[PDB]
Image 1 (cartoon, rainbow, N blue to C red):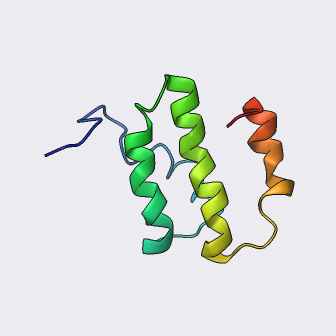
Image 2 (image 1 turned 60 degrees about the vertical axis):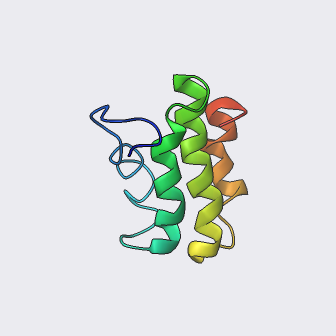
Image 3 (image 1 turned 30 degrees about the vertical axis):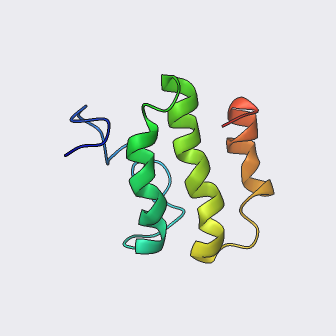
Length: 85
């Protein structure tokens, strides 16, 4: 059974077309541990602050994934997205 967001065309595509598109390469159960939750995150709040935070998770998670400096020098796409993302 689907917990939320049951067939809405672009469940498990949107964040793959943005984050892993260049940041995180391909196939990491590590990264997927947040790429799962992004699918549910689309109905978090409102279409902005939902999807926004769906990008948030992975940007923090990229640290354990292999990053040391990808917060601050990347906040230009999160904080200068939305002062929120």
